[PDB]
Amino acid sequence: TQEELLREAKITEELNLRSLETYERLEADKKKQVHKKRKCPGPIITYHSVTVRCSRTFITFSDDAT
Amino acid sequence: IADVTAVAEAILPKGSARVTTSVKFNAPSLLYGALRDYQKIGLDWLAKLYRKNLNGILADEAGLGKTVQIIAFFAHLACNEGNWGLVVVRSCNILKWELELKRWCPGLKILSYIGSHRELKAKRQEWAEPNSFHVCITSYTQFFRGLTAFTRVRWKCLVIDEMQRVKGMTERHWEAVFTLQSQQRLLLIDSPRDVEKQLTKKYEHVLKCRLSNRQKALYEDVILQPGTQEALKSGHFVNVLSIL
Ligand SMILES: Nc1ncnc2c1ncn2[C@@H]1O[C@H](COP(=O)(O)OP(=O)(O)OP(O)(O)=S)[C@@H](O)[C@H]1O
């Protein structure tokens, strides 16, 4: 029953680990930090300055209307 | 019957054997956390005790992590011996028991004996059905209520914990436990510093904080209060305790 065992044991893995809270888990996985979900701000204008030795700025418009 | 205890003691992890071996254990697919060498030795002793069809008491000192020892024994039993599926608990520690089961051995199905009368009947129905669960966790109150109803299902192993601090436990309940159809039984006792060379370090500090000038002024004000001098010398406990 080792094949059946592998099957429902992996299912049990998914079920049980989904109960824990990203802590309490011995294999403390790294760098979750759940970032923001952004969630709407309608149409937006993004100002993005990056290092490329050099610095560049990209202005993104969400839609063609703006 | 004493031969069982003699054999268990012969293999028991005494102090020297509690640390002096290098059994190159591999992690059963269920288990995840790394035990101590001494907890690994306890795991090996439990596995041998079950393998030789023996019932034994956990003679380890109190506070050394019996939960993980039982969890790792369960993992090794299920993997090596293939007995893929009971624990008796008192109170909230039912939650801790299942939490540690899910933590160290998340691959085992868990059955919880908490619910309403309708929910408890449904839990019973699911508990009699095949391949429904692997580990059953129950409260001592439920066990006493279902002293005989628990007799219906047969078990690979059974664990008793916290009984020593449970009111109402009686020799008749022990007789029922023996009547329970667990091919092997385990008993946890806190009174059967220990094994500290591999336990957590627990570094403790105290640092001296010089009183601020304001604090010193207030301190000497409260001391010099003539009422406080009178109370200090008189020894009146309530007054001196107020000053303190
Ligand atoms: N370095 C370690 N030192 C002590 N315990 C550890 C260590 N690594 C893992 N553990 C175990 O990790 C588990 C986490 O603690 P808990 O399980 O919540 O407490 P507990 O040991 O179950 O309390 P008991 O057994 O009912 S007295 C314990 O089983 C510990 O023995």
Image (tube, coloured by chain):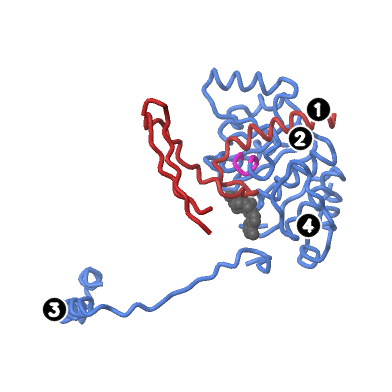
Q: Name the residue under label 4.
A: B41
Q: Where is residue B92 in the image (x, y as percent from the top left)?
A: 52, 40
Residue B123: name its quadrant: top right
Residue B43 lies, with reference to residue B211, above or below; the image says above
**Front position among marks 4 and 2:** 4
Amino acid carrying mark 2 in the image: Ser
Amino acid carrying mark 4 in the image: Ile
Q: Please state the chain letter of the residue tagged with numbered disc 4 in the rendered image.
A: B
Q: Are marks 3 and 1 in contact (CB under 8 Å)?
A: no
User: How far apart in space, not on screen, are marks 3 and 4 (Cα)?
Assistant: 64 Å
Amino acid carrying mark 1 in the image: Glu
Residue B182 bears which disc, if any? 2
Q: Are marks 4 and 1 in contact (CB under 8 Å)?
A: no
Which shade of the palette goes to chain A?
A: red
Circle 1 sits in a helix, a strand or a loop, which is it?
Answer: helix
Q: Mark 3 points at which residue?
A: B225
Amino acid carrying mark 3 in the image: Gln
Report whether the residue tagged 1 is closer than 8 Å to ligand 1.
no
Q: Name the residue under label 1.
A: A4
Ranked by sequence position, the earlier of labels 3 and 4 is 4
Ranked by sequence position, the earlier of labels 2 and 3 is 2
Q: Please state the chain letter of the residue tagged with numbered disc 1 in the rendered image.
A: A
Give the residue drawn at x 74%, y 60%: B38
* Frontmost residue, A62 versus B243: A62
Q: Position of residue A3 (x, y in %)?
A: 83, 29
